[PDB]
Image (spheres, helix red, strand yellow):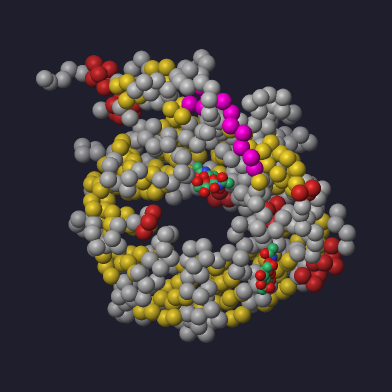
Amino acid sequence: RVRDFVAKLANNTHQHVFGSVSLSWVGDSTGVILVLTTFHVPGQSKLYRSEDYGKNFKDITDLINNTFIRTEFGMAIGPENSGKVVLTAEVSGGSRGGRIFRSSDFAKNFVQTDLPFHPLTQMMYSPQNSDYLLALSTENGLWVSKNFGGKWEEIHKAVCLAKWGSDNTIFFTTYANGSCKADLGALELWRTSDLGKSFKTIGVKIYSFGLGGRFLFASVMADKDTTRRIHVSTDQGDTWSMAQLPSVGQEQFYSILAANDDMVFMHVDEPGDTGFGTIFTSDDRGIVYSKSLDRHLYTTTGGETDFTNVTSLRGVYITSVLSEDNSIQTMITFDQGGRWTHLRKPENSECDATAKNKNECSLHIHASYSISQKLNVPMAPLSEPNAVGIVIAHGSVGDAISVMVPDVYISDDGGYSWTKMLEGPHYYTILDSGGIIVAIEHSSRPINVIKFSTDEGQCWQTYTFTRDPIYFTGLASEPGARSMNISIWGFTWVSYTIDFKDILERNCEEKDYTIWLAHSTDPEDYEDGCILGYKEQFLRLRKSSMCQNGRDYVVTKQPSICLCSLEDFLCDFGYYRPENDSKCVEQPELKGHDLEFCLHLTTNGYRKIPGDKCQGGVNPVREVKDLKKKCTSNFLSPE
Ligand SMILES: *[C@@H]1O[C@H](CO)[C@@H](O[C@@H]2O[C@H](CO)[C@@H](O)[C@H](O)[C@H]2NC(C)=O)[C@H](O)[C@H]1NC(C)=O
Ligand SMILES: *[C@@H]1O[C@H](CO)[C@@H](O[C@@H]2O[C@H](CO)[C@@H](O)[C@H](O)[C@H]2NC(C)=O)[C@H](O)[C@H]1NC(C)=O
Ligand SMILES: CC(C)CCN1CC(=O)N=N1
C-alpha cells in the first residue's frame, strides 16, 4: 500500500554478473562481502570483494596469486570489527608445511604465509583477542600464533580437541597412546592460561568436553563400565561437581541445546535407537536439573533437531516431540522450559487431514528435521532480537507435521498467536529491525519478482526486479537485520541487490512507536505478563506507520518486578512436585540417577529459577539440611 514504489526501487536496484561457492560478511556497518568459488577441472579459485553491501563487486583473485583455496577450511572471518580474513590454500602433495593467505584490512590486501604444519581444522580466532589463533595439525598437534598467523609454536602434541575459552584461555584433550579412537574415554583434559607456557590437568578419564555460558562440561567414563556421565565446573576446572543428570552409554549422546549466563538446556538421548530424548533445564550452577520435555526429537549426536530459540521474545522456545503414535508435534515454551504446550492455530485456518477434529487442531512448524527429510521447506523459522515478537516459519495446521507443501505463517507477539502470511514455500528476510519484511517465492521455474511488506507481513506489494528471469538460489543480507539492502542470488550466476532507502524516506519519531506489554495473556490481572518474575513493556513501531528505524535503533523496554511466588522456584535435590498443587516436598526415597547423585548435598528444598528476578512476596527457601544420612540409612556400612 505504498504509492509509486516502482519508481523508487528501479534506480536503487543494482545488478552484478560473475563450483563450490561461499559468501562471508566481514565486519559490521562495513558492507564488506567476500565470495569464493573453487572448481575441480582435470582448477583455480576466484575471489570477489564488495564494499557496498553487494551492489557492486570487484574481482581480487590477483591478491590470492591464482592459488587454489581449499573449500573445506572455508574463509575464516575475524571477530566483530577486527577485519581479519584467512583463506587456507592448497599446496603441493609433498610440501613440508601448509600455506595460508591472510588479511587484517578487511581483505583489501592479502599476505601469503607458509606454515610449519599442515592444518587439519579451521583456524579459530580467540574471542578476547583477534590476533591470537589456534589450530590442529594433521598429526594432531596444537599450534598457537600470537601474530595473527605469522609464527606458530606447537604448545602440545596429541591434542584430540581444542577450544578457546574466556580471557584467552585454552582447553584441550590429549591422548596418551595410539589414536583418539583408541583412547576413547581415557583422554585427559588440560587447560593452559599462558598460551602453552604452563599446563594444568583438570580432568582424567575424559570422553569429551563442551562449553556453554559460564559452564564448562566434561563427560567422564566409569571405571567398571562403558557408561559416562557429565561433570560441571564454573571455575575453569579448578573445582568439579557432578551434574544431577542420568548417565548414558556409548550409543547415547549429550547435546547442549542452548546456554546463556543464567542456565543451560541439555538433551539426553534415550537408550536404544529411539531417535528422541528428554530435555533438562539446569539451575544457575549447572548442577541441579529439572525435567522439562519428554520424547524430544533428536536423530543422533550430530543429527537434526528442531529446537529453536525464539530470539524475538524473552523465554520463548520451540521444538518438536515424537508422540507414542510416532507422529511429530511442535511444542512451545514461553517461560524458559517451565511449561510446554501446543502452538495455537490461526483463527481463519482449516485443520488438515492429520486432525481428528476438523475445527480443533494446532499449528506445527517445519524446521531442521523437515528439511532433512527432503520436504519442500526452503528455510527454517526466522526471528531477530531487534524485531520484537516477530517469528516467521513454514508450517502446517493439523494434529501433526504434515508432508503437504507448506505455507508461511507469521507471529507478531512472540508465538502466542499466528496468521497465514503467504501461500506456498517462500524465502524470507527481516530488515530495519522489522521496518521491512522481504519474501521470495520458491518455485521449480525461474522467478522475476520480489515481495516486500512494511506492516509486519499484514500486507504485501509486488515488484519486478529484473528483465530476465533467473533460477533462485539464496538471499544475502547483513547480519543483525539492520540494513535496508537485500541481495538475490541466482543463475540464468547473477545477484541483484535492492536498496529500500527511498521506500522509507521518513525516519521514525516518538509518535510512530506505541506501548506493548509482552507476554500478555489476561490484561485485567495484576500479574499479567510476568515471565521469570518480571514484566517487560516495549515501544514498537506501529504497523500503519512506514518509517525507517535506522541502523542505530534501540529497542526500548521497561521492566516491572513482580512478587515472588512458589511458581518462581523449582525443587532442589531430594524434592519433587506432586500432581497436587505446586509446593515442593521431600521425596520418600531417591531412585535411579537421583540415587547415583547421592553417592549440593545441603538442600534448601527450593531454588530460584535461573534468570528469575522476582522480588518480595513469598520466600520458600529452607535452612540448609543434609540428606546424606537419609541416603545411607538403608546401607550397612563399616565403622
Ligand atoms: C535465546 O536468545 C536470546 C536472544 O538472543 C538470548 O538472550 C541474549 O543472551 C545474551 C547472553 O546472555 C545477552 O548478552 C543478550 O543481551 C540477550 N539478548 C536479549 C535480547 O536479551 C538467550 O540467552 C538465548 N537463550 C539461551 C538459553 O541461550
Ligand atoms: C546499503 O548500502 C549502502 C552502500 O551501497 C550503505 O551506504 C553507506 O551509508 C553509510 C551511512 O548511511 C555511509 O557512512 C557509507 O559510506 C555508505 N557506503 C557507501 C558505499 O556508500 C547503506 O547504509 C546501506 N543501508 C543500510 C540501511 O545500512
Ligand atoms: C555436555 C558435554 C560433555 C558434551 C560432550 N559430549 C557429547 C556426549 O554425548 N558426551 N560428551
Q: Position of residue 372 (x, y in %)?
A: 55, 50
Q: Position of residue 339 (x, y in %)?
A: 55, 29
Horizontal arrangement in the rendering, residue 544 relative to residue 34 (left or right) = right
Which residue is painted at 67% across and 38% down in the image?
Answer: 537
Horizontal arrangement in the rendering, residue 72 relative to residue 227 (left or right) = right
Which residue is painted at 45% across and 20% down in the image?
Answer: 620
Horizontal arrangement in the rendering, residue 385 relative to residue 539 (left or right) = left
The quarter of the image holding the C terminus is top left
Which residue is painted at 21% across and 37% down in the image?
Answer: 224
Which residue is painted at 62% across and 74% down in the image?
Answer: 51
Q: Is residue 558 magenta?
A: yes
Span shown in magenta: 557-569
Q: Quick check: can you spot residue 560?
A: yes
Q: Quadrant of residue 593?
A: top left
Q: Position of residue 131 (x, y in %)?
A: 40, 68
Q: Quadrant of residue 1?
A: bottom right
Q: Quick check: can you spot residue 395?
A: no
Horizontal arrangement in the rendering, residue 155 relative to residue 168 (left or right) = left
> Does 538 sit above or below residue 454?
above
